[PDB]
Length: 258
Ligand SMILES: Nc1ccccc1NC(=O)c1ccc(NCC(=O)NCc2ccc(S(N)(=O)=O)cc2)cc1
Ligand SMILES: [Zn+2]
Picture 1: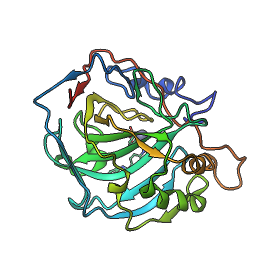
Picture 2 (picture 1 turned 45 degrees about the horizontal axis):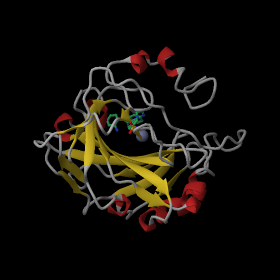
Picture 3 (picture 1 turned 180 degrees about the horizontal axis):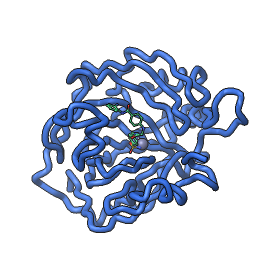
Picture 4 (picture 1 turned 90 degrees about the vertical axis):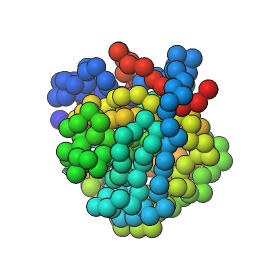
């Protein structure tokens, strides 16, 4: 009886195995755009993905992860609110059963169809497992998805999903360029928070881009054909794999822009 997104094991249950679910810096949150303060001391984000080395795509039973070689400084995030250098390890998405829900963060209570998370770890902690034990261990770049025009740089991801339909399936996934998933603007909001899935560790500097990317209805439909279940288990569509907004508590969201 492991955590998930169903009636009996969904986000309102997680606190029983992971009491930090009710902690002081949980994610996601609603971004109230009128209360976020412009911080003119915040630097432009530096997204350096030209040498990124993707390896593999994995269905882990709660999303799919595109994994990268993080054994050297090849794809790094720096600048913005960050001190030092954060290495890209994986990206994944959260999405809905319907185009009106799926994002984890919300903007003035608006839900997007999906949310991309580019996960990075602070190189001063040496590995990801050490970094998640630190309050500044991770930097997650969050990008909203809205349904409209197709995102051409997403299609290589969409087309491999048939090969990883069920929990525990993986496929080689080399030479994928994550620059093709970024919007034009790197204007962002930032706040201190957590992993949005168990173990819900309070180790994340969240950086959420203001400009969504557009994906097509056909692209997001292909996400919704994935399965939470393993092969030969009853089919349960991988949809609504999002945690809702958590209390902001004693936090301020800062804006990089006016
Ligand atoms: N790599 C490493 C290096 C040295 C030693 C140990 C390791 N650890 C692993 O290999 C490993 C760690 C965790 C794991 N599952 C739970 C978890 O912590 N998920 C992360 C996550 C959850 C959530 C988010 S979100 N949605 O962006 O907030 C973003 C990220 C599975 C595998
Ligand atoms: Zn995520």
